[PDB]
Length: 146
Length: 46
Length: 49
Length: 54
Ligand SMILES: [Zn+2]
Image: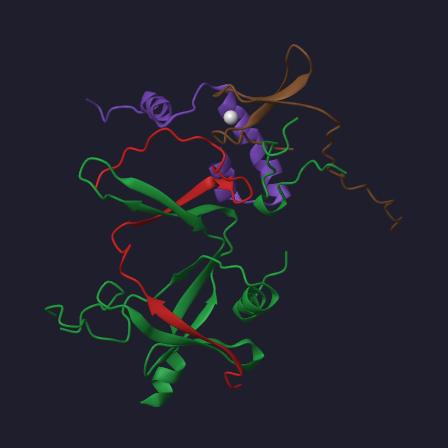
C-alpha cells in the first residue's frame, strides 16, 4: 500500500491511524525555537487590527482606516519579547500585543497569483502556512495613559 | 519584564500587494500536500 | 461530510452519536447541493395556492 | 471508526472487491485495500456490583 495516501483519521492532529510499527505553544517560545533552535525561515499569518496607529500618507484622506496598503516599504515597527512571556509589537508611540491564533491543522498554502498579462497569468506557490498570530491593541495601557 | 532578547524588526513590502492570495483547504490536513499532484488549469475572475 | 463532521465536533463520542445521521444520509442518493435542495422542495407545501 | 475519502471528503464504507476487503466511497472511484488488522474498541461501561441497601 502507498504510504502517502492512507486513510485519514477525523482528528487532523492524529491522522496516523495505522503505523509502520500536542501542548499549546506560546509566541515567545515559538519565536525562540524558530530562531535559536533552528535557522530555517517560516511563513506566518498574523491578523492586524482594522486601523493602524498612523495616517494615510498623502492618500487624499478624515480619521479613516489606515491599513498596510497605505504605508510604504521599510522598517515600520519592532517586535519586543519581554520576560514572563510578553510579546509586544512597538508600531510607533503605541505598543500592541501579539498572541497565538486558532491552531489550524488543515492545509494552508500561501501562493502568489500574478496576472502579468491580461490573458495569461502565473500562480506562484510561495509556501505553506502553519501558525497564525493575532495582534491586538493594548487597551489597558491606552486607557491608563490618558 | 524588560525586552531582554528578540528585538525583531518589522518590514513592509508592496510588490505582491495585489497578487497575493491565500488558499486554504478545509478538508485536507496539513500533512498531505498537493505538491506531487499534477495540476492542469485554474479558472479565475479578477 | 468531513467538513460537516469537523463543524459538529472532533470528540469521539460526538462522532459516535453523529454516525447514524451520516449513515441515514448515505442511504439516500443525496450528495450535492442540487439534490438536497430538490429533496427539501419536495417536502415544501404551497401556502394554499 | 469513521473514515473519509481524501479525494472528496465523503464517508467511506467497507465492501469486498476482487482480491480483498476495501474501504470505498460512493461518489468517487477512490478505494483503499486493507493490509493488516484494523480495530475500533469502545470499552462500554461495566455495570458495577450494586450494593445491598435497606
Ligand atoms: Zn471519496
